[PDB]
Image (cartoon, coloured by chain):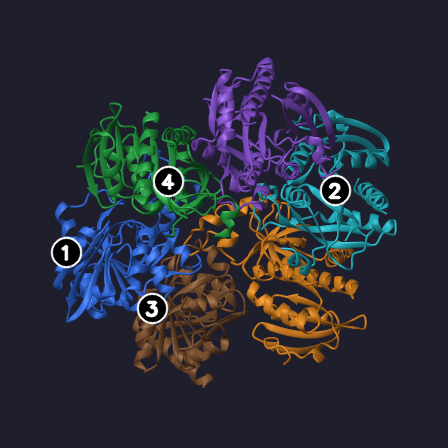
Chain colours: A cyan, B purple, C green, D blue, E brown, F orange
């Protein structure tokens, strides 16, 4: 008996949580949950592994999205049905800008919509823009730990032009931000995106990014 | 090891050239069990791979995970490993009043409501299934006296708005998809799923054979809810059909 | 007095026929009709020349479509209003694949929609796919006479990229399949497409293709 | 012989540079009869060509057949033969309440609801008629006291769904064209036809002159049905107008 | 107190005028008005400067459109609300055709729709065609003063392919015709476009073009 | 002189790298007056430029005129003159019931309903504002206790149909925009304007910083009409905010 079709969760499981951190894989979910108090694994069905934890005494959810905009759309929709209104995504990616060094942190203000799923929420002309408060929290959290931060646009497609985006200032590439940002920005949900640069130390970069997204969640509670 | 995500080497396939590709890795073992000498090869994320034997020949069973992006990764890596024939199998809901639970659907082509398929071919190109695979699937279904429907499937990048569901958080659908289900229905589309566009398009445009069969476990256009047992029985029948079709494609 | 705007035919003229073979020109119509019993010319208005014949005692219609998707759409719509539910197209074309030899037979599973008329029936994302039963009948008919058959995708445009389609496995080019297939597949009508390869013997190739489409009709009655 | 489909040689035209291009080959003889020394040149499929003399100069009358694809073949081959001025003539229905049967329409430009025109120019390019041809047609119509309407025509690749007709086998229209007639009507579009987009676009983008005139023989927005005689009279008037315009374009 | 949002005019100000000449800038407005009788400046707000004058005893309006389709759409809409039904645009541009000499006059029959604003009035497939009567008046007016005239297509975009348009017979480039023509042709308003070629004498060319548009207005009253 | 339209030389800016860019040139003087040593630089068409001093550093105030095309000219020429930070300021109407007159809006990104922005980047690219500019604007608004709304703005190439207004000459809206306002409203769009798409897109794609703030002087979704005084007060507050944000961006 679940209130949702895929996550296998019930309203009561979130214990009032209104904020969820949504990484791409289950292993990262555990890492994120482990940084908080009272970490507990709630469920695991297909790409969707969900844990629950507490930040400053407040319940927070951590759930994997799977690969690409399609899987992400399912996780975000169902989590929203469960009461979540703030989504913070964290990941690791490469950089396409020479001035960006490995170990730096990227906070996405908006994404180039090169995917298919974002179109199921709004026409292409609509901006895949991140929530101002979430973006602010991510930037302050990164600064609170002395991380070198770059704030700007990310390219988001369904594949795992090139010099074009680089010439337009695009920082990096990934596959879920366009769907996540568009979904939330066009449905009254708050969303933020942060990523550790692992290529253009890897585990350290992931750790620092995991810490930043958790500290940002704390500023958002 | 030869492929990143799947974590497999070409030697692992033992020369297999045909793979049954279910969506859920938890269904791989069951499908493989129907055949001889079933052995687990790997399991990373939602990519579980098992190898088995069908009539003396090695066969692969590998999960794709959810969505076109995840599917493209699985398909391309399997192709790199020598797989040239892909048989998609799963369960689905139907959007036609005459299609009942327990029935089986064999997809001839899919409406491309996705993004990943666009990376392998322009929208003008048809997400069509291979004739031999489709034939094998249809004949296999008939061999077990299953009520079969052969037609178009709508392959969507989302489970909710692209399938015009309003029972959601926002309760709204973007203009582009408003009234789209009624349209597909009037055009004879049998059901919605989320991986076929990518699988069929990339296979049809790269000289690879692909087909897809699915058992109906629910029909949103019917008031009567599905039976708990009839649904489980449908899953078993679908697996039986895909394996039987594989035998004819070896 | 006609029940249709262009064909100049009445419901009674089909004598219950529910299947029509639709070549592009009047000369081919005669050739096709001649292979069957009780061949009789029903009408001829502009691009639309229609004959009636009998296969295994059942009435079958043969009607020319004219050039391109626009003319074809008229012939298919009006024939459908007259009771036809199964359409088999036969033609001769060139091949763009090295492995395809002159004299071979091409059975189309689906077409690349590079035309304009198919869009008047369904959005581009909808597949211009042939009916499974019709495709099966064409393949078996070709095999029944020992014809070397290729089954796959055909490119269909309004003109009488190149290496692109060839790289994607496209077998040949023509101008009516996209409209025909899309029209029928999106309106509950059954349609099939077969073509004799005359370039990459010509009259023999047309004859063999004409025989195949007639034998396929027989398997569809 | 110099051209495949038309089956004509350049010598056959005797230097003609202007051609009247009706849609139906059965109307070619009649149009040519209005002029001097009418002679049949060829007849293949729906491509009938006749040559005649207007004020001492050779003129061509050639049918295009139905649809843009067929029209493009006729136009390009005639262009290869030296034709640089094309005058489209025919009969049509109207979609404006104020336009009555017997009236004549002169098209300044067409809405491009086709595919063939896209092969000669991007959709952004206007399917506009040549000013001199349009002027000639308008003045010719006035010379015979005909009620003339000069404006936009909608050129569709289909006779049914693109013209939003519901009296069909399916009785349905694809989303894209649902409510399209009301839209064109509110925008001042006079009528629907199926060849102008291709003719005007390819001529305007290749330095060739083209115009189009048509007599109204029916109006789907009016309850009153057309007279059997008034319709025949309209065809004759339209032919008279196109020939008179040709005289002014020599 | 104004009947419109931007022009700052009232119905009474036009004194029954049903025709307006719409150049791009205020300086040109004055020049045009000066050629007529009883010239009087009515208003000036932002890009919209309007004068009133009389031609053969009939009131005519002259109003600047500003730059591009967006500003033009505002001026045309509001002038139409005020009673204007005929719009004649005059400007100066360069030529992209070798056979076109400086000092020649260009009368636009239709425009290539490379802008954004025309789409807010009709889908791209709709022709940005000029009114036949207006085009005729401009051609006759140019001839009445012995000006060498070219009649054809103009490219209209939002920026201040190249060999493509030139190969397709495009005479020149500008930024307002597409919006103006489409707007009027799809809303029952009459519109014409004339331009003096100043590059491929400048003041003389502008003068001759100004005279032509005024003489065309006279033939349209 | 170095730039055509603006009629300015680089020396005129005295090294200024930040410019406040209002739409109306009649508002330039007022904005500049808030700062020290205000001086008029030039005035051509709707391009009025004034230079001033903020905390010892030279600042520019330049009008853009109406529409994306006009704005692109102003922005590119200012960029050529060394401007790397652009602060858009003005007044606007709102389309959300909860947003009242007197409130201030800070735009994070805009829906691209224009054409000029397409010349600098594909539609897929977001017309997003610079984070530092947006932060500065938000904090400045808060420093004066203003009720602030931070979100998406719809940037349209037309004032009427693109903003789905029916109180017009034709009283009709093209299919594409029918019901579009309701759609934007349901998506959280705060208001409509006509220049942001171009400004944000070209700046975000060329390494330049841009932000936008606007005071609400009207709300078409509310029955109550705006006060004549409350509106003037709103304009002053908006100017105060943009200047204060500029101080934080020097």
Pointer 4 residue: C195
Element type where label 2 sits in the image? strand
For residue D30, which numbered disc appears in the image?
1
Identify the image quadrant of the N terminus of chain B: top right
Q: Which residue is mark 3?
A: E134
User: How many other residues sit within 10 Å of disc 1, few (<14), some (14-19) or many (≥20)?
Assistant: some
Residue F227 visible (yes or no):
no
Which one is in front in this view, the residue at disc 1 or the one at disc 4?
4
Foreground of the two, B193 or C150: C150
Locate residue E69, reporting x and y percent: 49, 63
Relative to F98, D230 lies left or right: left
Which is in the foreground here, disc 2 or disc 3?
Answer: 2
Front-most of residues B21 and F38: B21
B160, above or below F136, in the image: above
Q: Are marks 2 and 1 on the same chain?
A: no
F242 relative position to B205: left or right = right
> In the rendered view of the protein, which quadrant contains the C terminus of chain B?
top right
Nearer to me, C6 or A61: C6
Do discs 2 and 4 share a chain?
no
How far across and how far down the image is residue E123, in percent?
A: 44, 53
Quickly name the residue at label 2: A89
The answer for how far apart the CA atoms under marks 2 and 1 are is: 75 Å
Q: Residue at x 61, y 16 (%)?
A: B232
Mark yes or no: residue C182 visible. Answer: yes
Relative to F17, C29 lies left or right: left
**From the viewer's perspective, is residue D223 above or below residue A98?**
above
């Amino acid at each position: 008996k679940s209130d949702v079709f895929h996550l296998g969760l019930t309203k009561n499981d979130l214990q009032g949580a209104t904020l969820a951190i949504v990484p791409g894989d289950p292993d990262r979910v555990e890492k994120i949950a482990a940084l908080m108090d009272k970490p507990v694994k709630l469920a695991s069905h297909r790409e969707f592994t969900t844990w629950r934890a507490e930040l400053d005494g407040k319940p927070v959810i951590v759930c994997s999205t799977g690969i690409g905009g399609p899987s992400t759309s399912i996780a975000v929709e169902e989590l929203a049905q469960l009461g979540i209104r703030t989504f913070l995504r964290i990941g690791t990616t490469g950089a396409i800008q020479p001035h960006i060094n490995v170990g730096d942190v990227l906070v996405t203000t908006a994404s180039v919509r090169l995917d298919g799923a974002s179109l199921h929420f709004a026409p292409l002309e609509f901006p895949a823009v991140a929530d101002f408060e979430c973006t602010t929290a991510l930037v302050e959290a990164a600064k609170s730990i002395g991380a070198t931060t770059h704030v700007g646009v990310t390219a988001s497609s369904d594949t795992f032009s090139m010099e074009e985006w680089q010439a337009m200032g695009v920082m990096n590439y990934e596959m879920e931000s366009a769907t996540l940002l568009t979904m939330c920005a066009s449905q009254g949900l708050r969303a933020g995106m942060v990523a550790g640069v692992i290529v253009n130390t890897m585990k350290q970069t992931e750790s620092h990014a995991v810490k930043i997204v958790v500290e940002a969640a704390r500023r958002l509670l």
